[PDB]
Image (cartoon, rainbow over the protein chains, first blue to last red):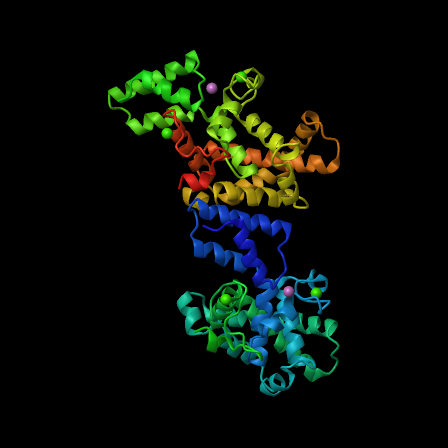
Length: 242
Length: 242
Ligand SMILES: [Ca+2]
Ligand SMILES: [Ca+2]
Ligand SMILES: [Ca+2]
Ligand SMILES: [Ca+2]
Ligand SMILES: [Ho]
Ligand SMILES: [Ho]
C-alpha cells in the first residue's frame, strides 16, 4: 500500500526532478487509494506511475541507445530531460506542443542526420538500402521477430503497413518542410531515421520487445533517486539489465 | 434467527440513538420472521437492516473521508447524525425534505468550498483542471476502474454520462441559486464538489468499490453499540478495516 506522497516522489525522480502537473497528481492519488483497498497490487500501481514518464524520459533513453549504442548517463539524462542549464529540454516550453510520436521523430533526426553523434555511423550503415529493408531489419532489431509472433501480433501485416507508399510520401513532405535539407541523398537518409523513430514509438506503447523491456527496467532503477550502474560515459542497456 | 427486538437495537445504534419510524419497524419485523422460517439467512437480514441507515449515517462517514482524509470519531458522528446539542442534524427536522442524493451534495459543498475543514486542501488540488478529468479521476478513486469492469458495469459509458454538457449546466444553475457564491472561480470549484458528491451516492447505492465496502464494515462494527477503533481525532477507514 502506497501513500499518494510516495507515488509523487517515484514520479519526480523518473522525470529527473520535474514535479507532476495538477491533473496527474489526481491520477496518482487514485492509484494510491486503489492499493489501500486491495483493488490493485503494489507492483501494478508503480508500473502505471512510471508509464506516465514515457514521453519525457523513455524518448531519451531509447533513441540514444539505438543510434549511439549507449543510453545517456544519469548526469546526461538530467540535461536532456529536466535541467536549469538547457533552456529547452524535453519537459520544457519548446516541446509542449509535440505529441509522443513527434518527440521520437525529432530526437531521431537530430542524432542521425545532422552534426549529431550518430551521423557518421548511421550514414555508412544505411546507404544504398531500400525503404522496405530499412523497416524490416529495424523491426526485428527493436521488437524481435520471434517475440512478436509469440505475443500474437502478425509481423508481416505490420511491416507492410509501415513501408506502404502512402506512408513514405507523407514523411518525404514532412522532412522536406521541417528539416533544412535540400539534397536528394540527405532527405532519403532522414526519412529512414524518421521511420526507425516511428518503430521506437510503436514499441514503447505496446511493451513488447527487447528495447522496451530494458528501458522500463532502467526507469524503475532510476525511480528511487539513485542509478546503480551510472557509468560516467554511458550505460549500455543490454549489459546492465539482463 | 433474530427476534424483531434485536434488529431494532442494531438499527438504533447504527443511527446513533435515533429509534426507527413506525413504517420501518414493520420492515424490520418482516426480516425477523423471514429468519425464523429459514427463507433468509442471518447475515443477509442484518445487512438489509444496516442498508436502511444509508441516508443518515453513510453520508457522514463517506464525505468526511473523501475531503478531510479521515472518517469522524464515534463522538463526532453522534454530533452529525443524532444529538441533543446540534439542533439541526442529519436525522432531524432541517433535512427531512432532502432526498438521499441532495444530502450527499449538501455535505460535499459544506466541507469543500466554504470555511469547511477541507477547503484549503481541495482548493489547491482541483484548481485548473477540467470537468472531464475531475469526474474520471474521482470515479477511479472511489469505485475503482479494474473493480468496476469485473463487476460488469462499463466505465466509459458512465463517466461520459456524468460529464455530458446537460449535466454540468443543471449543476451550474443549482449551485448559483442555492449557494451564496457569485465569483466565477468559486462556482466552478463548487460544481466539482457537487460532481464528486453525485459519485459518492452512485457508489453507496450499488455496493461496488473500495469506499462503499469499507463504510459498510464500519457501520457493522458500530451496530453492536461500541466502535472498536475509536481513535479520538478520527478513524482512517482504509487502515482500520482491510
Ligand atoms: Ca530547462
Ligand atoms: Ca536505484
Ligand atoms: Ca438534534
Ligand atoms: Ca463493535
Ligand atoms: Ho533536474
Ligand atoms: Ho445520540
